[PDB]
Length: 180
Image 1 (cartoon, helix red, strand yellow):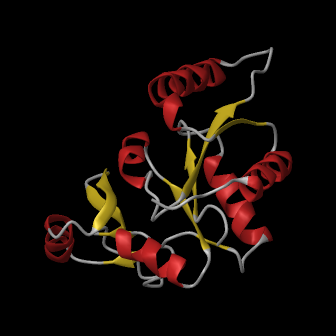
Image 2: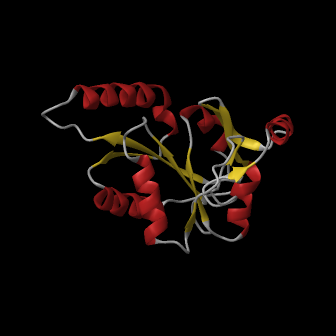
């Protein structure tokens, strides 16, 4: 670590942020790790504890939340989800880069020297022929960019995953971090 320790991706839902993250992990599995989240969702018979999620009770989750153990947590379809501080710390302990796909309001919390984040905004491509779906995504994206611009180290348009990755890793690798 002579540079940034954590890659933070911000964007409206539907921009392809998840594809970017998965492509990075798939391409450099020894460098990047995505912290496995916690959920109160009852697992299905088929799922493996600690693969896509750590499955806990609402009682444990509640204790964790009030113990300030979550960098981020929230409710989806009536179940609780969150990412623990400690899961990101364990990645940095192994000298790997944490990839965090967080919500914009969590930006106030991650911008620290300890986490040394490189914060990348991912925008949709401005395509000429527009669906109403692209138009809404562009509006959602501009709403987030407008409020949180001062947080971003880099704004990129998603012009395809392999092309976005190349630009993204180069900008990441070039980034400086200093202590204090």
